[PDB]
Length: 253
Ligand SMILES: O=C(O)[C@H]1CC[C@H](C(=O)N2CC[C@@]3(S(=O)(=O)c4ccc(F)cc4)c4ccc(C(F)(C(F)(F)F)C(F)(F)F)cc4CC[C@@H]23)CC1
Image (cartoon, protein in one colour):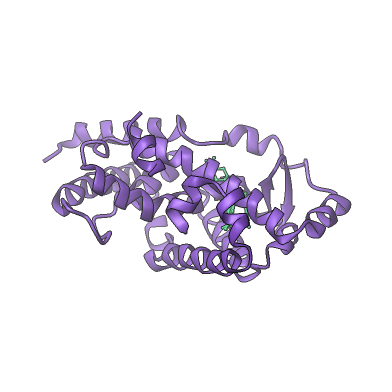
C-alpha cells in the first residue's frame, strides 16, 4: 500500500496543505523581528487584569486552532475518517499542532515571541499568573528552534502530531493507523532525501506535548474557578469546547 511516487505526492500534498493554512507567513514573521515592545508597553501588559489577559490569549489561541482545523480538513485522508474520529483527533491534537507552529513566531536570539503586532519576552504575560506554563511554552519553542526546521518539515511533523492512531476513543483505529504509516513513510522519505534523518533523535518526546496541553487545562480550571462568568461570557465557544458543537459545523464546510 503506497509506492515511491505516491509517497512523494503525499509529501507535496502535505507541504501544500500546510502553507495554505498557516495563520502567519514566515516571511512576514521574520520581516518583523525588530518591532519589539517598549519597556512601557510591557509594563502596560503587566498592569492589565488577569481576566483581560486570559481573554486576549484564549482569543489568540482560538484563531490559531481555527487555521489548524482548516489544515486537518485539507489534509489527505482526514475527511475520509468518520466524524467521531475527526473530532477525537482535533480535540486531542489541535493544541499540540499550535504548540509546534508557535516556534515560527519565536526568536531564539532575544528569547521573544510575536504577540498582538510586536515581539516581547516571557515577562509580557506576567498578569496571567501561569509562570510555569509560560516558561514551558518558551522552553518548548526554544528546543524546536534549535532543530532549525524547514517549513516542509513542520508540515510533515504537524500532520503526524494530528494523525495519531493511539488517541483514546478512535472507532476506526486501523484506518488512522494506515494514514499515520503513510505520513510516517512521507516524513522519513523526505528526511532521507534531504539528508536530515539527524533530527529524528532530537524531535521532542511524545509525552512533552501531552504535559504542555495538560498544564494548559490545569491553569484554565484554576482561572475558570475564580472567574466563571468571564469564561461563560467573554471566552470563545470553540476554546470552551476543546478545553472546558463548533467542530461539527467547522468540519461541515
Ligand atoms: O502561523 C501560525 O499558524 C501560528 C502563528 C503563531 C501562533 C502562536 O504563537 N500562538 C497562538 C496564540 C499564542 S500567543 O501568541 O498568544 C502566546 C501566549 C503565551 C505565550 F507564552 C506565548 C505566545 C498562545 C495563546 C495562549 C496560550 C495559553 F496556553 C497560555 F496560557 F500560555 F497563555 C492560553 F492562554 F491559551 F492558556 C498559549 C499560546 C501559545 C501559542 C501562541 C500559532 C499559529
